[PDB]
Length: 168
Image (cartoon, rainbow, N blue to C red; front, side):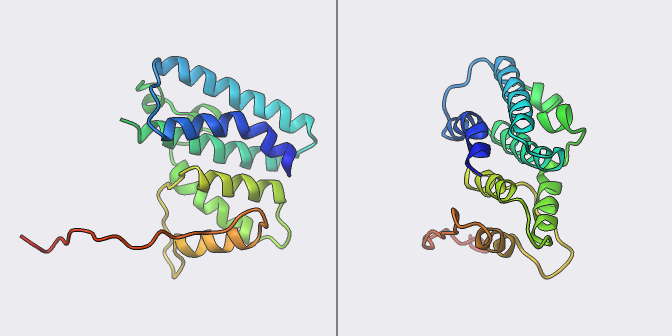
């Protein structure tokens, strides 16, 4: 849905700016704005008629997206207690969000709005820590998720000349 994208757009733009190495001063001031944005999104999703189930997955992916873009930045408030710990009680969102994307793909008709947010989460730079004790890889999960949403697709950059370790 678009009403869902409307709710996350300010936050999505904020993560996109943080990802582009924008000056951030202050750190604790950013965590507070982050918190208010998550709370604003929660109240708005509920007002828009979205179920707790769908609101919680959308907000989880966003918390995991925002936490990752702050921690992989060149504070210690998030390092100490991130949004995934503050709002969800986990420090393993990098791993369990991938687990959460896969169980959404196992559903015959998952909420299009949820799938949109999960695509937006990956588009803005979410990597996490993917694990799967089986034949499934990220590349395959991305393609499968991409295939079920018309608004999104996948694109690969051409290979680049890289130095070769096993040298010198």
